Image (tube, rainbow, N blue to C red):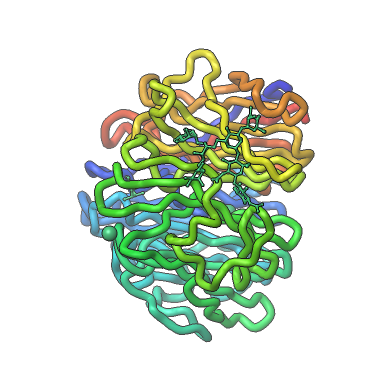
Length: 419
Ligand SMILES: *[C@@H]1O[C@H](CO)[C@@H](O[C@@H]2O[C@H](CO)[C@@H](O[C@@H]3O[C@H](CO[C@H]4O[C@H](CO[C@H]5O[C@H](CO)[C@@H](O)[C@H](O)[C@@H]5O)[C@@H](O)[C@H](O[C@H]5O[C@H](CO)[C@@H](O)[C@H](O)[C@@H]5O)[C@@H]4O)[C@@H](O)[C@H](O[C@H]4O[C@H](CO)[C@@H](O)[C@H](O)[C@@H]4O)[C@@H]3O)[C@H](O)[C@H]2NC(C)=O)[C@H](O)[C@H]1NC(C)=O
Ligand SMILES: C[C@@H]1O[C@@H](O)[C@H](O)[C@H](O)[C@H]1O
Ligand SMILES: [Ca+2]
Ligand code: NA
């Protein structure tokens, strides 16, 4: 496997602040291909300057040929909270509508949707008028909408879109799912699907394949990040209403963080494992988790694998040259190709201030981690475009550079693979 070509584009100047607001691990998602176009969302500084930001949405044609980016600026909502939780997630439903939810740390939902199905019936003009106003509810559904953190979207097989988030706080919170119908344009409440018990679950993402929805998490006792413990897993066969553990045992609704039956690896507190890192269902139905810990005596990224025979394995990701991360260092992701043979670790290196692209193969039990490429000059939790990789064999990664404001840019990097 080789990188046929490497290309990059600078899409904006990052915003100034001691917190990172662009390029955050739990953006789900930041960079999305739908049809012949790729979309990206990020904050850029408003004319009022420091601590005033607008959400931007970029689009570019990627098929049959790659076109230039164009951007719209949502200049009717000013982000002002210098808090790294307050990121943007985007989703695109099967009616072609683009959804955005953003700017939360334990506050009411902020959500907006495009007026029309702009990703399906593609308009000539890319302007802010394409979007409806910010609202603080989900039409057709019901609260609670506050105190909300961590909006995550997941597109389903019938064109519908899940929106998932935590209601509560670090160390005492629960998570909820809502479902947007592409046929009616209405949201519906699926209710609380995971319930804390003087703690909160921190999921790594949502993954969906062939009618099944997969998630993994750690449990946090207090606002101190050293109090994460456990690696847990569950899946649903009905888009988040009913859940099962790794042994196919049906779980209570909601899943309780006190239910040990979803635990797949014992990791104590003070292991230097961080919440909300990465996960992946590969196209062959193998489930993967990316975390980190100090338990070997060295800080190392860790790969958890749910094998076909039901067994789980854990193996350090330690290819030559990769510096292992401690608790507060930037978090990585796992990507997979259409065939399911290639597993990509998109791993920020805290020493090099760059993002490494490493590859392992299913034929070698994913133990053959090899350096494949690098994105230089990043201070980012890298995020990729699942659909572009599956459809075109191009690994496309959104990054925040390292360096100082206003030199520090936002970029998209495309690694064309010889798949
Ligand atoms: C339902 O699903 C669950 C989840 O998959 C399943 O439970 C697993 O069952 C398998 C098979 O019986 C267990 O696998 C064995 O594990 C042996 C060691 O287990 C200990 O270590 C686990 C790993 O953590 C270690 O390392 C970390 C650092 O990464 C460290 O923090 C830990 O402390 C520990 O050192 C650990 O998760 C596990 O904890 C469970 O069990 C204890 C009690 O023992 C409990 O207190 C915990 O709360 C938790 O439930 C435990 O501490 C391992 O030696 C053994 O290896 C042999 O077999 C393999 C075969 O592949 C050989 O390769 C190998 O050489 C040995 O011969 C084997 O891998 C696994 O531990 C269970 N996992 C959990 C989370 O419980 C249930 O069985 C399923 N139930 C049904 C009905 O289907
Ligand atoms: C460790 C800490 O945990 C949560 O508060 C968020 O994920 C935050 O981004 C991370 O820095
Ligand atoms: Ca996802
Ligand atoms: Na608590």
